[PDB]
Length: 264
Ligand SMILES: Cc1nc(Nc2ncc(C(=O)Nc3c(C)cccc3Cl)s2)cc(N2CCN(CCO)CC2)n1
Ligand SMILES: [Zn+2]
Image (cartoon, rainbow, N blue to C red; front, side, top):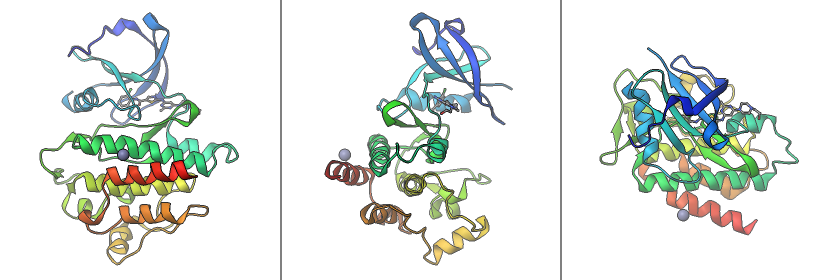
């Protein structure tokens, strides 16, 4: 676009995460001594859809695009580099004396502020999870993995038939009828919050995948994690209302966390 770069501006240092689809590297942009992350693929417009969505989004809590290389293979997307990796591994491995309750709360305020931004732009993410969040210094958390993100035309996006999703993060109307909406991102946010409050447990632990929809339909929701405040649990419960209209908006979610945050 106007976001092209010459391949030779960047030195690929080491690999961070390979794919069945494609791989991820850390590199240096010589011309500024800046560390960047570089995503790539081989044997286009899918990989590119992610590029196109990140062009349009500019919020301090969404991993920022720095450029692209998309006239010749290998094709590159380049972004700022998050030094402490994905949020899930960060939670599982941190010092709990260093990440307190108040840090966990801060992390959630950041995420709700990125989604507040994206809801107003009418983008859906479609893969909210703690594995798809990235961490930086000072406990900056940034939302990432935008490869299923889409600008919606109205209020619902329907994915193709035959399309399979991570069950424990996906809203029931999405599992039943394949319908995504901002409200289905709300649900996954809920599930993300519980991953945070538990320092990185797996959702529905010890429940067969095959039973989740049904359990849900008959009323079951995950329980309050140990140490999690009532109001944060009630918020996380509102995210899981069976009816998408009944769930909160990301404005409201953001409002509730900023408020809790300032009151500590
Ligand atoms: C897998 C991984 N990513 C890291 N940082 C990233 N920054 C930006 C990344 C990225 O994916 N951006 C991006 C997005 C969001 C969309 C399209 C295209 C692109 Cl390019 S990935 C750090 C890291 N860690 C290795 C383990 N170490 C543990 C010690 O704490 C520390 C570092 N591992
Ligand atoms: Zn707000």
